[PDB]
Image 1 (cartoon, rainbow over the protein chains, first blue to last red):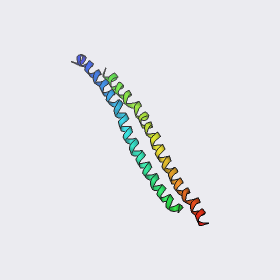
Image 2: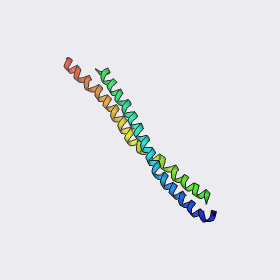
Image 3: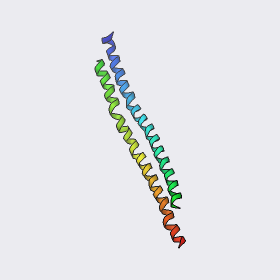
Image 4: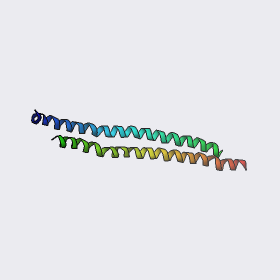
Amino acid sequence: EQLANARRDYEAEIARARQEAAKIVAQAQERAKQQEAEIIAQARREAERLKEEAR
Amino acid sequence: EQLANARRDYEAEIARARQEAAKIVAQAQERAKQQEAEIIAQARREAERLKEEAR
């Protein structure tokens, strides 16, 4: 059983590597969107405060 | 075979995360720097113009 299913285990390992190859990109893209939104919002609030202070 | 199968998935999942997160860096830095420069621009638009009009 183990020797016969070792081929299936190797195929499943390759499939898991392939699945992780895209999940790594997707999670990083989600974090990118979150961080960019946070930075943009903070700097826009800073810009509004700077406009008032400059007035 | 089990050790090699685990190692393949681990190696596939280890490297790509930092490279994918680097895709964050360009957009997030562009947004943050552009918004800080917009804060500076809002500060500077009033500073010279209001002084000129107040003269």
